[PDB]
Image (cartoon, rainbow, N blue to C red; front, top):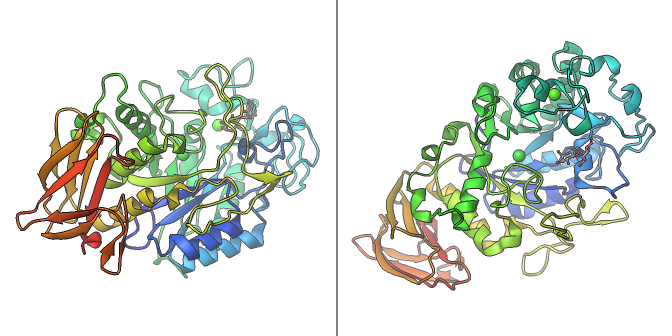
Length: 496
Ligand SMILES: OC[C@H]1O[C@H](O[C@H]2[C@H](O)[C@@H](O)[C@@H](O)O[C@@H]2CO)[C@H](O)[C@@H](O)[C@@H]1O
Ligand SMILES: [Ca+2]
Ligand SMILES: [Cl-]
């Protein structure tokens, strides 16, 4: 459950948030495969509640109605088509599994679901599965509201309703079997792993029980005996009775302190500075690297919905964002997930975004197609950070120096730091309010390298900056604090 199941040489996965199956399938063939991306985390593929007030929010996909592969992203046949096409070109698919609960207990009964299945929250009736009042924790929860009220009580956090969401009785074998039946359907189709949503709200033991009933990955694409990659969404910042380590036996966990801390460091908040990143990783109290799934931002914190807070860096802060993602992809700590978002009308009212619910670009509910501009960018309001040259080239950088030790560290005691990865890559950052101009030891073989942040290497030429490494491995670097991108990265595959 700890290995991504990616093809050799691919070290990152990208979250194509709310994308349609047909668009992901094309992206796999025309872009992800040739650019070295390892896999794609997709939005929940199972039927959810269609919420019209507000109008089709992104979070409606976290309110299951059944396990039918029928959503705004497409139907079962399109889902199968995408997984097959992606696998065939070497890019894995990771499914967002919402198995801790069903929909809001106050949602009206009827057929307001992405696939028209009938449901009745009030009587706990989900005939499309089927589930009944017997399959929920209504009797198990002890709070007077039926919802979670105190997060210092590990018991209610697991047996009570998370913000009113009908909480499934995951201890019952019937329930575990229904969920496993859904998950095995996905595995046989070709998926390589799963993101387990709201894992902190499920007992680690119930999760194991469910994982016990799972098949091995599809033998047409994976080696015999391969287990699905598992990463659980556990929001664990400081002192809480529940800890991330409680889930190490099921697979990896999301390390939410990663982005929260990196964000305040890059922003230079509360006295933090880049020179402190010298012992980044476990040194900062993070979970062991072999159990970590890291990221700068996620879909549920880039819009204030969760762990991270105000330090969280997103595409809205493009300059600092690229630099944070650049640092993450260059540093050996954890397995990295890249975010891919859509733009929405941010509308702050007293420091809070009142439009944080807004769903993907659409036309009366129908998700808009991801268009590709002649300059390789995306249209129709899709940000496509994974297509930004600076992010894209850092994704390749991580593949190139994979397995190389963190070495040749340098810092000016403030926010000008550099470090290498064995003799395969080197990166330099300038986050101070003055220019950087110094000759550094790179640990790389002499030669001319193309800077992959400002440009690309093409048939024997660079389209951006060029770095000259001498016989002694030294190279001069000049970065203005006013530079578009105050960082430079070079690697073995960018050598001319
Ligand atoms: O009880 C239903 C619940 O739905 C929405 O909650 C969202 C939550 O805001 C998102 O962060 C994500 O976790 O999915 C949840 C389920 O859709 C509403 O925002 C919330 O007020 C409401 O009670
Ligand atoms: Ca629960
Ligand atoms: Cl996550």
